[PDB]
Image (cartoon, rainbow, N blue to C red; front, side, top):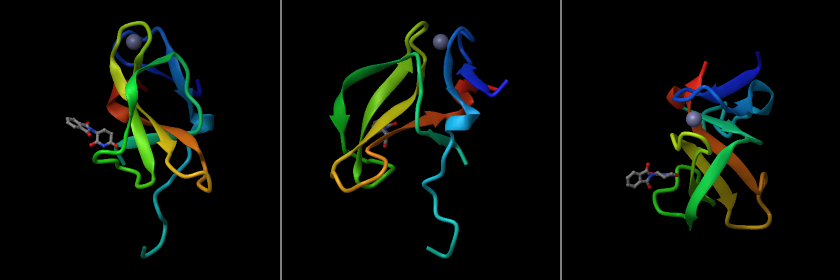
Length: 97
Ligand SMILES: O=C1CC[C@H](N2C(=O)c3ccccc3C2=O)C(=O)N1
Ligand SMILES: [Zn+2]
């Protein structure tokens, strides 16, 4: 009901609408959902900063633990003075609804 599930297998809740937050700027200074918390995702490999969509963070591939659908990434801060230190960037089209 606030629940966002893996579109491919529909088994797993990956996150909730309660966890959604925005890193995009609202003044003169979409496709990827950013949430504080997620569940039922397996991380693949090790963090990388290459081509990072969120400067200051590294990314690790995150896939549904059941069906292995590539749902998004875990982003982890490269510096201690950043907040949050970690979040999830999820491909919207990989989630239901
Ligand atoms: O923050 C991110 C997450 C990883 C994402 N990524 C991809 O989706 C991708 C596909 C193929 C080759 C290389 C990449 C890449 O770095 C990307 O470009 N930036
Ligand atoms: Zn799945």
